[PDB]
Length: 131
RNA sequence: UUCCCGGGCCUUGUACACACCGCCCGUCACGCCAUGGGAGCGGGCUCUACCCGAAGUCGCCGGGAGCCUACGGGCAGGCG
Ligand SMILES: [Mg+2]
Ligand SMILES: [Mg+2]
Ligand SMILES: [Mg+2]
Ligand SMILES: [Mg+2]
Ligand SMILES: [Mg+2]
Ligand SMILES: [Mg+2]
Ligand SMILES: [Mg+2]
Ligand SMILES: [Mg+2]
Ligand SMILES: [Mg+2]
Ligand SMILES: [Mg+2]
Ligand SMILES: [Mg+2]
Ligand SMILES: [Mg+2]
Ligand SMILES: [Mg+2]
Ligand SMILES: [Mg+2]
Ligand SMILES: [Mg+2]
Ligand SMILES: [Mg+2]
Ligand SMILES: [Mg+2]
Ligand SMILES: [Mg+2]
Ligand SMILES: [Mg+2]
Ligand SMILES: [Mg+2]
Image 1 (cartoon, rainbow, N blue to C red):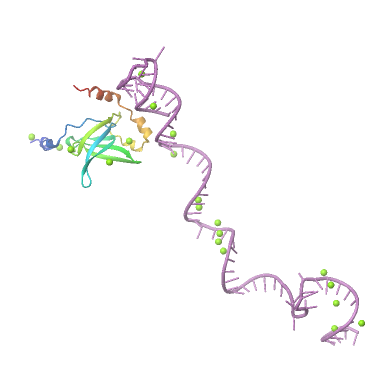
Image 2: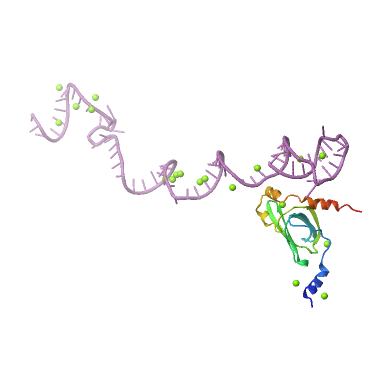
């Protein structure tokens, strides 16, 4: 038997392919399904992805933002059915996979440390030319 | 005729005139009032140094690059 393939097989029913590719440092908008009262709604969480934790179907990513003077971090399963869509709002270029360090940085310092990833921005623009 | 008691005349000092049985000082005791000191406690104002920093004018850029061309330009946008 191949235990890995069995697991991949169980996971296959839940795997997602509709979400855009992004890297740590990119700024991302996650439209997330949420439950309140008496209804469910979609709430956008927009911020820098500081971490992508890979384990295939089980990979998760972490998005950090400042909300009314307070740092907030959300952890999302990359294949969650509660993510309606993810929008790339900016491409950042980091020089490491985990950006924990920006927790200690001023907004000004972060803006210096993560400059726009012009290579991947151009790529986005080259695509998005629809036939 | 020094002393005690009463008085008369002259004079002298007096913070006494209720007139020396006068006036009056301070502790202590009780009561009230205001202030000072006092481990500290609370608050107001202020000064200095540094960290972060909105809006905004100003200055640079405006390109791996968008839009308007009015194209040796402008706006977006970026930096300070
Ligand atoms: Mg396994
Ligand atoms: Mg199998
Ligand atoms: Mg909301
Ligand atoms: Mg942020
Ligand atoms: Mg849905
Ligand atoms: Mg006599
Ligand atoms: Mg006589
Ligand atoms: Mg006499
Ligand atoms: Mg005398
Ligand atoms: Mg006299
Ligand atoms: Mg007292
Ligand atoms: Mg006192
Ligand atoms: Mg006192
Ligand atoms: Mg005092
Ligand atoms: Mg005080
Ligand atoms: Mg004080
Ligand atoms: Mg400091
Ligand atoms: Mg400053
Ligand atoms: Mg130009
Ligand atoms: Mg400007």
